[PDB]
Image 1 (cartoon, rainbow, N blue to C red):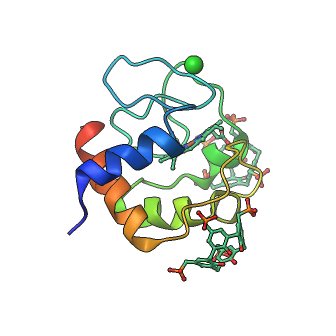
Image 2: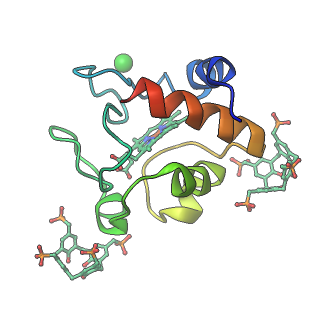
Length: 104
Ligand SMILES: O=P(O)(O)Cc1cc2c(O)c(c1)Cc1cc(CP(=O)(O)O)cc(c1O)Cc1cc(CP(=O)(O)O)cc(c1O)Cc1cc(CP(=O)(O)O)cc(c1O)C2
Ligand SMILES: O=P(O)(O)Cc1cc2c(O)c(c1)Cc1cc(CP(=O)(O)O)cc(c1O)Cc1cc(CP(=O)(O)O)cc(c1O)Cc1cc(CP(=O)(O)O)cc(c1O)C2
Ligand code: HEC
Ligand SMILES: [Cl-]
């Protein structure tokens, strides 16, 4: 079982620079992530995505989010998300446990 509290710290240190999670939170370098799970990639209104992210056209879930976060440019070549990857499966599980609740 992932640990959301550890996930929240991982989000703060690794993601928060570029992303907010709450409903009505602002777009920053990256898009606000409210409602990300169960939505197709590249669909947050008011954000200018790469065609790479739009045409990947993946329905985000816990599993493909983990694949993506391992290595974003591998999963979506051409993406403008400048993030190398979360190496540790436990860190991905914790982060995603947090993100599923925080973006709900
Ligand atoms: O309008 P935009 O800009 O916001 C976004 C956009 C729209 C289109 C574009 O050609 C490109 C970008 C260029 C492009 C980029 C990549 C990414 P990359 O390889 O990294 O460079 C990849 C592709 C691109 O063509 C390969 C590609 C992938 C699929 C799978 P899928 O993504 O749908 O699941 C289907 C098509 C397709 O060419 C046919 C197609 C279908 C529809 C839907 P519809 O029928 O509603 O019109 C619209 C367009 C299409 O070409 C038009
Ligand atoms: O499978 P892929 O391919 O999609 C993704 C992948 C997997 C591995 C890779 O070596 C690379 C890429 C190459 C690489 C990339 C970056 C990122 P960037 O420089 O931006 O390009 C950074 C590094 C790379 O070596 C430096 C690096 C950083 C840390 C975090 P930290 O210690 O600084 O905090 C930990 C390791 C590490 O080498 C050890 C480590 C742990 C685990 C998970 P586990 O231990 O569970 O096996 C797997 C691999 C590891 O090397 C294998
Ligand atoms: C800035 C330096 C970023 C950091 C750090 C992280 N992300 Fe990001 N992300 C960023 C951009 C600029 C974009 C859009 C990319 C594009 O090619 O258009 C993104 C995108 C995402 C997405 C996809 C969103 C969608 O399809 O609507 C997700 C799910 C995402 N980012 C998550 C995320 C997480 C969890 C991060 C920390 C591990 C993270 N990103 C870091 C910019 C930046
Ligand atoms: Cl900001």
